[PDB]
Length: 172
Length: 180
Image 1 (cartoon, rainbow over the protein chains, first blue to last red):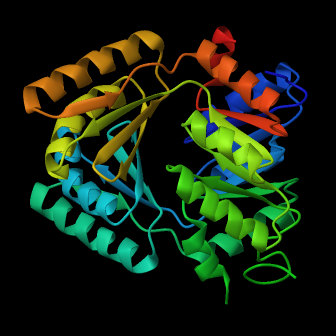
Image 2 (image 1 turned 60 degrees about the vertical axis):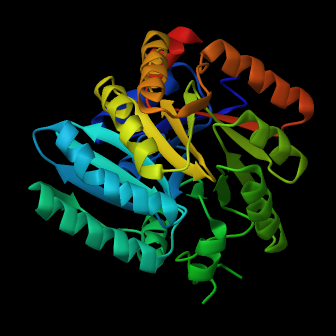
């Protein structure tokens, strides 16, 4: 890899870990550091601390299930993941402590609404807690992008798993 | 001239990087084509599948985004609930080892991309996948790999095929630097 020519992207789920990773790349002389995150706060912090490129998720929803037993969180999530996959979604799973984060992309608003209703009902049936839902709205995305630009972002990038869906939300 | 709004509450076809995250070659090509026809000037393609990135550089993907390490396991079967029931036991282990897992469906294939874990963990997850498939009567059609050495070889192939810009994504550069 070329520290001068290649873009090195930090995929960040926590602000402090993000800052440490950007610092490592800076101290290695990386000239093009990007930060990719679903958390606008992380992208806002990166902008101030040497993130040259801020990578935003376009139109993705995140559902977070919280509970003490990971097997039960996953058991509860399986039916919703099954439906999401059948609707054409891409699903990303990660663990933040006792939280199971389920990011769902590649689906339109009415499908995101259905999946959030499913998550709510599954959490009740399985006795777990939903601590985050939704978040794919395009208007919110553009507002947040504008905040990044006005704070001084050097370069914005937007990632989507289905620009056919995203162009329909942006056409108006 | 902005997309979605004005004053910066919009995307910029020339100034912003627009990234296609593609799980299938045809879907990538269609989305790249749409972005080109809208006049997008900085189109990137992100994929865990090298074939997708090799095709993208030919069709207007100026930035190719690769994962730093990562393995894809593909399970094949007619009943998705059974594919997912089998996969969750391995996904649980992957998650406890710190992985990020991406799931997508390509027809009768459940593609499970696992990133963020070292080779010995990938070996263990592949062994688990084999055992789960055998016990549950499903077929694994792709497994293993994901090492940084292979990533570097594949990046060099992309460069030699004409990639204009490479980007590499990781959730832990503190570790990845040791492999590089």
